[PDB]
Length: 393
Ligand SMILES: [Cl-]
Ligand SMILES: [Cl-]
Ligand SMILES: [Cl-]
Ligand SMILES: [Mg+2]
Image (cartoon, rainbow, N blue to C red):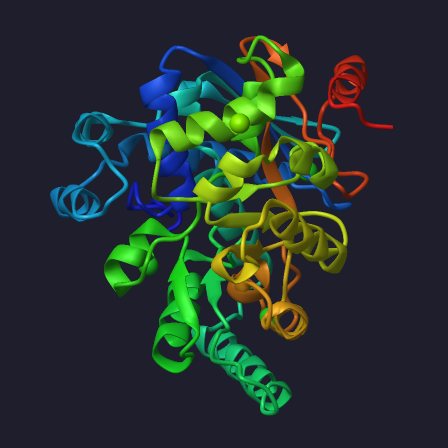
């Protein structure tokens, strides 16, 4: 139905959103933030504004169900104070401003971080579904399934000569999925047909398909700490410590490129390297990055085979297999694939859209990374300050 909701579950979002939301609820309940939409491509999405606005209002109706509560209570991640608060949580549509200027979609979101944090993934998934169902009216679940099966055949062919049994794939594709139904179809097909699927970031699919919910933290956790910790140069160490404080023995993958990998390794001391299970790559050459990670573990006396590298920088299954060949004899590996799984249909172009943190406590925050052109920060002075504090060139 035209005006009917695209989203019907509060769990149709990525696990890292709830994992971070709980940390923010426990530690930073009164901190405010602002976040903004960007369309990375040369695309104009202004025409979709009214429909996006309508869906944003609809999201005000989403509410945790009792079955969902019981499911979350079964997992090792959640405390009951948070779960009781989550049961009362409702999106507040007023937090989201949708405007159009020169045909460009402008979306800004502002309010308490523990509330605002929940918008990013479902709002992106709603924008994605709105745009695709308008532009690509002929797409069937069958087309999506057949493309997936062709790729799984190519994967099997290219891996026949190696021990592929340590290959691990995560679905990370909620945000820019072609639609909710396409994601459901491809993830269910993977569970039934691909031994190496280890889980999905989507909490609703983790529950309903009986898969492990995966995902730890995201850049906003590190970025927000740039306006939380008194010392800017320590903001990433504080973010790593507060995460362990919240999750001492679960969710132990640290994202490495809010600043740069080199800066990260300067912060990643023996205690962090022992308590965390592993590291996630999101920018720069993955070969160089993985080698840096392995060498760091060796320098600290840690057996790299007892740690994990997570790769998820807009991967496809072929690139993931190539990375596996390079690293699998030396360290444990997980590969998160996003749009290449949930929006890979003949004659359909994926959208390159994001919603990223721009302020915390009314002050700028930024992600640098090891890839140029990934900075949304519109405060060049702050970016300069951040570079200085982290001793970057
Ligand atoms: Cl746009
Ligand atoms: Cl579904
Ligand atoms: Cl792929
Ligand atoms: Mg220390």
